[PDB]
Amino acid sequence: LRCALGVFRKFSRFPEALRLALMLNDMELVEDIFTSCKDVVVQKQMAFMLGRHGVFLELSEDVEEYEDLTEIMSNVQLNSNFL
Amino acid sequence: MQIFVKTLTGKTITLEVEPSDTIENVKAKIQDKEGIPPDQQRLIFAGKQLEDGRTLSDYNIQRESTLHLVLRLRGG
Amino acid sequence: LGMILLWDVDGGLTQIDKYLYSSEDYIKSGALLACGIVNSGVRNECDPALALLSDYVLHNSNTMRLGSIFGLGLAYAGSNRED
């Protein structure tokens, strides 16, 4: 089901290991199928429970699947301005 | 005069220019220091986009003011 | 004025400058502290060392020394940048 990974391993981020959720942030960028869960899992990674993620999505597939990051960064924030 | 070109990589680039110089000459100087062609270069001054057809004086760019450097980012 | 233009990057800097220029310790330091409020959550290139570092290095005195470190620690509170 794999979409409650981001918000509910913020549960597991700070107590166990700060790399462990970062190893689960690795589990985000592995299950790359396809966009719909992929958009919504990383919606929260900018301004909903933590930021500091904008350095891990500039990999060699910068077309739209890794160009989500800037759209995660401020454009859905601009959609939250469009609110 | 000297100016500052600040990247988003925490790196500050200094260039010796004249106030009447065009923006594309400055991008040519950036290519002289770095080897990045000007079509891959974007320059921002106080949140404003710079056009190569104008001069530094047209945007009131003066001695040692701070620019921003963002790169062309295309994929696929 | 930082609360008035909230979650903004577009023209939040432009609204400050019409009331920034007064040559006062209390007017500029309150306005430039509000510049960290506007880009709160944007964390793009607004001023990592541009506007509030230039505010901070004016210091020999009152709130120019004070009201310049509050805004950037506010705007980059979600940041974990070391520099």
Image (tube, helix red, strand yellow):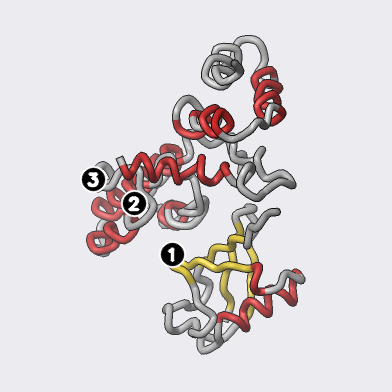
Are discs 3 and 2 both within one chain? yes
In this picture, residue B75 sits left or right of residue A44:
right
Is residue C83 positioned above or below B57 on the image?
above
In this picture, residue C73 sits left or right of residue B4:
left
Q: Residue at horizontal 30%, vertical 43%?
A: C6
Secondary structure beneath label 2: helix
Mark 1 belongs to which amino acid? Answer: Ala
Q: Label for residue B46?
A: 1
Secondary structure beneath label 3: loop
Q: Which residue is mark 2?
A: C32
| Real-space CA distance between mark 1 and mark 2, rounded to the nearest whole angstrom | 14 Å
Mark 2 belongs to which amino acid? Answer: Leu
Residue B63 placed where, x, y %? Answer: 51, 77
Mark 3 neighbour class, 10 Å CA radius: few under 14, some 14 to 19, many 20 or more: few
**Sequence-wise, which precedes: disc 3 or disc 2?**
3
Q: Residue at horizontal 43%, vertical 67%?
A: B48
Is residue B20 positioned above or below B31 on the image?
below
| Real-space CA distance between mark 3 and mark 2, rounded to the nearest whole angstrom | 14 Å
Q: Label for residue C4?
A: 3
Mark 2 neighbour class, 10 Å CA radius: few under 14, some 14 to 19, many 20 or more: many
Secondary structure beneath label 1: loop
